[PDB]
Length: 38
Length: 38
Length: 38
Length: 38
Image (tube, rainbow over all chains, first blue to last red; front, side, top):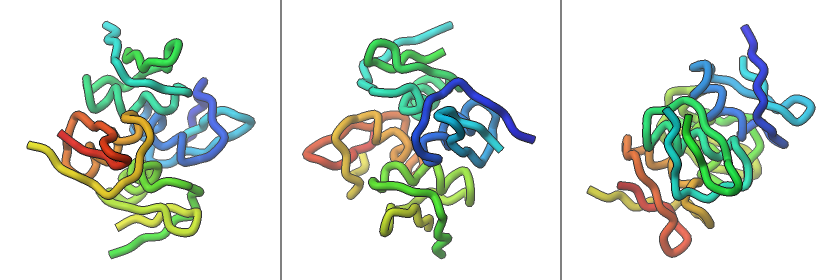
């Protein structure tokens, strides 16, 4: 399942560390300026 | 609890690798230019 | 061996979280604007 | 011990993912334009 975050982004690569750290998730995408995790 | 670092940052997404490496912490923030780890 | 991604990058340091999360790979490189993992 | 990389950097936050991923190191520092790990 997916998760939102409060971490600002312009590109997907920036989302991989928060998504791993916070949720142990392996996939991240930048959506309307914030990281989501999948 | 929280731990500071000496590591300069322009955005919070940059602080997650720092915080995991340095402290095993899963959360962090770029706080007025330096990573804090929570 | 190599597993290319469609994750945008400008610098190889940006690719290591990508490559670790997506493939368990401990190396990579930004190659023509995209992360490549080995 | 220390490890060198051929990964370009302008700031030491950028070295933490490579140093963790390649070497399991907990510290990184940008030196003469390249990440070093310890």
